[PDB]
Image: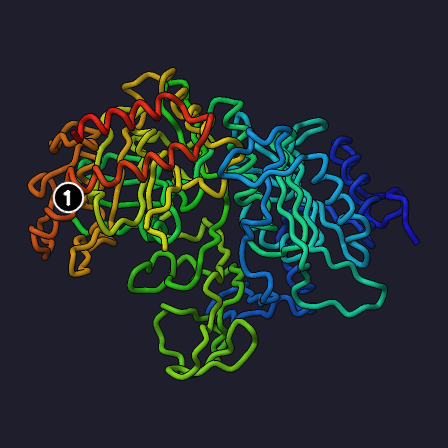
Amino acid sequence: SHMTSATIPGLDTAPTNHQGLLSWVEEVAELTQPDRVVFTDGSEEEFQRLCDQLVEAGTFIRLNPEKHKNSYLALSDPSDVARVESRTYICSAKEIDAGPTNNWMDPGEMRSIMKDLYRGCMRGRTMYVVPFCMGPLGAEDPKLGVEITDSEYVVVSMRTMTRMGKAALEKMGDDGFFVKALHSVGAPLEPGQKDVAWPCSETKYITHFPETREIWSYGSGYGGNALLGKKCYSLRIASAMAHDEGWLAEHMLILKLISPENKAYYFAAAFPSACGKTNLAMLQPTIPGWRAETLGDDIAWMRFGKDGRLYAVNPEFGFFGVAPGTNWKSNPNAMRTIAAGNTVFTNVALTDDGDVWWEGLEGDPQHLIDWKGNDWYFRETETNAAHPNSRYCTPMSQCPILAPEWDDPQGVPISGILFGGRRKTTVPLVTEARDWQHGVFIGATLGSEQTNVRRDPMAMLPFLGYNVGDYFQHWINLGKHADESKLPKVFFVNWFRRGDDGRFLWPGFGENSRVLKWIVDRIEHKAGGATTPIGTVPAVEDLDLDGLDVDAADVAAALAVDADEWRQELPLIEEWLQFVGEKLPTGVKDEFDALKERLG
């Protein structure tokens, strides 16, 4: 019953222009034993064909086209609803090159386990070969990949999240390099066996081989586990590439801010989860003459240009956003993006008229079908209607405030890099670093609230493809060797500082544009601030608070730098620096020592 790759339907008609690709596909198919192989082209005809098949399988239902054109709802197995960090691995030759922020296993050992799992795993299924490009196709060092998957849901979402199909395949030419990304849901079928809507396995691995730039995923069909052009490539493999190649692959939104002068400024900003980063990515300024446009809300790849500035490009082609919390009152721009359709929603609730809903959204719907397919009733049912990690997957080109530069292969020059977290105390509303190395320290020690303060360096804690210490040294090196006058200025922002009574000291949301204005003025040397032990911090009089109904005392409190509080912060930072381990750069320790000395 086992078939030699040659005889598997679809391989007879494979593209032969790139033999490295063909040989790999044949080797994989020989192992996994699919019923047939399909090379995807990313076309609209293909997209609708795959969607019809997904509706037939029950994986999708078609949403009301009057409310969302060409849009679908998928409900997952309740065991498969999120990234699984504990099952995510960096399999470098040596453990130290994974480092203390990563899960490591000997690559030989991992390969033995996963090759065993992959044997026959695609029986009864189509194996898709999905060529894709990271970033605009016009790039100079363009990063290509091919994802092999047995999940049609994956193919459809990869079409939205990446530049998928024909154009990428042509870019590979006859022997071009590409990231080999292998995926299976791990649910082989017998002939004539009825499938389920969302196949998956209890056994999961999301494995990365940084040296060879390979990704092997098994067992999950969900999000970042299975859409391998998301963080597996965009952050984990790409950070290793960037390490070796002299650039930066980072977990940052990309924002375009335009001043009343009509001059544009681009910012890259790293936040952990639960810090409202999507709200900031789609900022609507509240002060006259200031406008904002978005280039991305997840990943930024930064490379030096010929002029010595750092240029950012978004490697992604679509948004994969957490649905709950998204609503018309706080992110109308996200809602408008979704309104234009062409969206796959996963684990949200279904309204009686074929629309979608999730916690936080307006409407007070009286009845819903929840993410498990069950009746839900307003102000009665005690379970969430949409899964807390439910998703919309939507083309970026539909965003009404998308910057025209979004598809430029050279990207946009970055004026400022921002780091942020949620802190009830201690950390002011905004601080500017004293210089690049201090900036690296600020990013490296990024703290944010946890069940208490979690360190999430550059918001990359779960996503580094190599040792965290070496990553810090890489940031230090790029700054050392750059033209200092052209490096982005580094800032830290805390929108979330609280008074002792629990009030929010800063109103946030669109009002964050007032902080961004200070940042732009500092870049232009048009604003002052106080020199404090932690960096430059504005006084209330340094911010534009015109038209803002806010207690000046609350804003002063938001901006305060209390030496006692920062002395208490020191041992927390020190235990983190110790955790970083043997590869902690002396340059980072230097900045800790300097902070300690300034504090007295």
Q: Residue at x 69, y 44 (%)?
A: 182
Q: Residue at x 70, y 68 (%)?
A: 196
Placement of the C terminus among the 4 image quadrants: top left
Image check: 493 left or right of 543? right
Q: Residue at x 20, y 54 (%)?
A: 498
Q: Position of residue 475 (x, y in %)?
A: 40, 26
Q: Position of residue 85 (x, y in %)?
A: 54, 49
Q: Quadrant of residue 57?
A: bottom right
Report which residue position mark 1 lands on. 559
Query: Which residue is nearer to you in this view: 10 or 198?
Result: 198
Q: Position of residue 177 (x, y in %)?
A: 65, 28
Image check: 195 left or right of 205? right
- With respect to residue 62, does 313 lie above or below? above
Placement of the N terminus among the 4 image quadrants: bottom right
Q: Amino acid at mark 1?
A: Leu
For label 1, the crowd category at 10 Å Cα-Cα, with few meaning under 14, some 14 to 19 and many 20 or more, is: many
* Residue 264 visible in the current orientation: no
Q: Position of residue 37 (x, y in %)?
A: 78, 49
Q: Quadrant of residue 500?
A: bottom left
Query: Which residue is nearer to you in this view: 201 or 34?
Result: 201
